[PDB]
Length: 172
Ligand SMILES: [Au+]
Image (cartoon, rainbow, N blue to C red; front, side):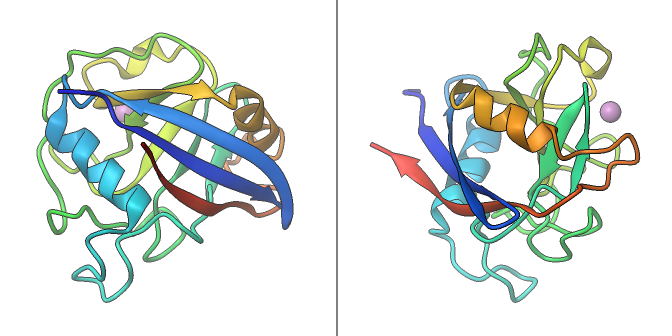
């Protein structure tokens, strides 16, 4: 299917830091792409958690230099929460796409078939995640914004300051 384009407007410590534009692989992983797209628009409203099914206002809570930036936990904000629009967890749709380099967009999980709303953007090639995380898009603009967020990560995963998805949505 035609490929959706979505964006995040990022703040770092409250400071406007630019836009990350992403292309989703609707044609390869439609269920996975459709979940992320709707979480960018917020169109499915309040989820089972009672919080909005929406990345807006959420943070990259886990950021590791030379690895990736991870976000999508809008229910607990710490890596233990998050919710897909389908309502809890859904199976890995396929592993056709691989972690080929910086910019790759892929699902975070807790093992096989545990996709929620958490995701990461790779800042390096992470071949060791192939077949274990579902890859469903890539950055096409704003890789420099991804690097700026990455600069605030630590080996420990804890960010130096709040890296927020201040706005987000779908481009037509
Ligand atoms: Au993994």
